[PDB]
Length: 168
Ligand SMILES: CCOCCC1(Oc2ccc(Oc3ccc(F)cc3)cc2)C(=O)NC(=O)NC1=O
Ligand SMILES: [Ca+2]
Ligand SMILES: [Zn+2]
Ligand SMILES: [Zn+2]
Image 1: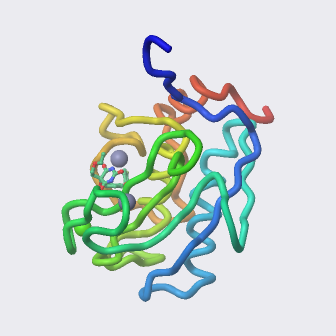
Image 2: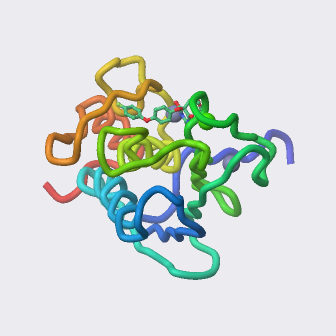
Image 3: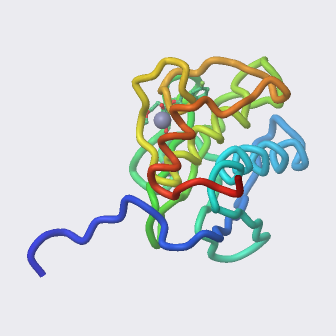
């Protein structure tokens, strides 16, 4: 029919994700904790829930790659592009890739996977870039460290504009 359909958000509250493969730089459990905790950033302030699948099709498919890696948005080696994620949808919708030419950590050396993933998952949920330099959806990496991390209020207001508040 006449104009193109669109999808700025997910129709459902309960999302699945799958970790298709793993960076060399962190243990499986490290990576697992990072992604679990990146998702809890968003689920904490919305009705959204996130579950892990070990195999098959999930809403959010997460993998690690270098250079041309299967979607024609190539990566660029260390620095520059760090990761990307597709907005909500069927097929590639919500899918997150991380540049394995980067050095990813659970600390302050290299790129802290959790921070960069909590940013990619906003994209995965339909958030674009913020112009608030303090905001997590601000396209500049700033390091924070797990126990000091609070979702700033611009990413709160952003995501709750799409999905409303969570419990509380
Ligand atoms: C539309 C794509 O623009 C390309 C730039 C890009 O790089 C980053 C990706 C995630 C980042 O994560 C953050 C963002 C804000 C923080 F405070 C801490 C970490 C920071 C940079 C990226 O590589 N991939 C992204 O999805 N967004 C980014 O901003
Ligand atoms: Ca890169
Ligand atoms: Zn990709
Ligand atoms: Zn971004």
